[PDB]
Image (cartoon, rainbow, N blue to C red):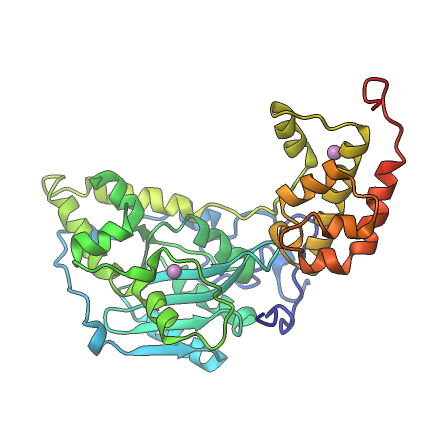
Amino acid sequence: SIIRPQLKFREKIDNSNTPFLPKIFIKPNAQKPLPQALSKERRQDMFAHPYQYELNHFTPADAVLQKPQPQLYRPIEETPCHFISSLDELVELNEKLLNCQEFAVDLEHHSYRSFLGLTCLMQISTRTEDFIIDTLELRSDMYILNESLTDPAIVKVFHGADSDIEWLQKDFGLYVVNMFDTHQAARLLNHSLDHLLKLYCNVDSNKQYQLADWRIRPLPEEMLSAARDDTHYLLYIYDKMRLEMWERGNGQPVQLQVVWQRSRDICLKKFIKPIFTDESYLELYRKQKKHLNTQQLTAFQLLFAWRDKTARREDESYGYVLPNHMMLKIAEELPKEPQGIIACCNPVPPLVRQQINEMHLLIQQAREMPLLKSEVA
Ligand SMILES: [Y+3]
Ligand SMILES: [Y+3]
């Protein structure tokens, strides 16, 4: 199993109910100032979206709203691929981007071995080159990209950026200003990229809807290729969509300004630390044939508490620590022995194995609870 890459992080992850605080500490392309509370030195509403104002006051240049002349995507065979894992690399790319008219953007995520989820890779494409960034290696440095991502002068093409926007700020403190979401454009014109790649370029990117562990290093050529495929064709599609969209408004920036309006709203989405109550599940088991008595129901609350505790600490997801069906099983079975717990999970999760004693005690506690009148055996 891959060594968890969170261990090499200079700054630990805050897995606490504590409210998420934006990470950005310097605001490039800042129409409105950024609170001094967010200053790198002092470490207004710090808990507010940092680029709230600029996104609310942004409009697509007339240059992009005019009948576009699509520029066919460069042949993958003749398109250079650059791997970026060091600060110099990152800083040099930014400069390059700052001189761009528009560029593609997509990310690679991972959530199984993480509590909040983790961005493992970022992809960007210019009209001529494909870039791949190691956002695990360059984690604390990524913020630099804000200079080019928050520049209303340059257009950032995305495909379904809803989640991306959220990740960019949770992990690096990166925000996007001036973004054209191709999934928003597909909604008007009337699934998406699978089609967008086959309808506009006549290409069938196989590993596109494939789930893979992006924490893996080195990244094999296959994933490197599947990663670049997510941004190599977006600028072309970006052009070809404003075309077949301008060819509908009779030559008026009607449906174009809408895609930009909607997309910039996705940029306003903010990240919020998730919260979980065992109430949700208990209410679900009730709709079902809930025969959970005082004891069993207690065990569930104790296991739910223990899993949430463990997950947040160990920085793992609930599924990894102990999945629903498995927790629920133990809650019902109420195994008297520690092995009775283990022999109730298929397969036995590592943390359960390691905290077997701890879990045993919880279940025992539940077994000492007083059974109601109607609950008597
Ligand atoms: Y992907
Ligand atoms: Y409760």
